[PDB]
Image (cartoon, rainbow over all chains, first blue to last red; front, side):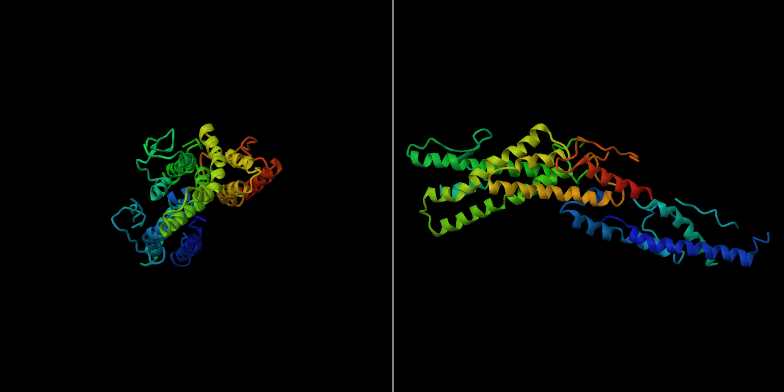
Length: 35
Length: 81
Length: 234
């Protein structure tokens, strides 16, 4: 079979972790929710 | 594209072996900037590149994830600060 | 005359056997010392090599001349390449026969013509029967799944070697249609273009009654279409 989707599944699993670690870093430290 | 063009012939393994090693530097590139926030490229032949921090430049493959990687590297480069 | 015949029949013409496109191979026919007994056998053996040259030249012309992707399937398409691929595998015992003849002639160069004719008599029937099956495809410019019926109507024959030989080619043409078929029912996306298999909700597709082969009923094609559309939805 031709697909590169068996490569994408361990990467999209990491993109979300990166984004959530960024938004928590905003919230509990730089107080955007307080702003 | 020549992969999806021919898969039902005897020229299937030759093209598969060629694409599998021809796609290694690109997969090497994407494996760095997402996990270490440092981009790499050969000659600027791949288009994607990189206060308020979003004043950075930007200039088949699965384009569903390609633009996602472009922000997913800049946030690592921000968290490295 | 001995090795010369094998060299010409394999497809390397000389001047004893002047290759023509209308007499095929034909012996020089002007020797002032030729014998009429050998003459009929010479003309009879020339036909196999003529068919062989036409077969291999057609296969060479229409297999591997592109990277696979016109709009006509009489000269192009994956099904057409699969036809020539099966035909080459059927041609292997002719090559084997000629290769045995060289060894016997090296062992004894005084072997008679009837011995050779006797061994080639099984191919003598097999080449003219299979000639019309490819001749109809080239002449009528047959496209798509209409190919698969054309060989199937000629594999209702009453000759066992011809029957098995055409069956080989139909199985070879079956592999590639199965190869797309394994993908479209599980996804809904095909990698083939310009060759139609009753697939053009019917979002960007259309079910054709014409192209559908004879032994695959319309109910079965409906079931295939239903599974592909349904997996494409969710």
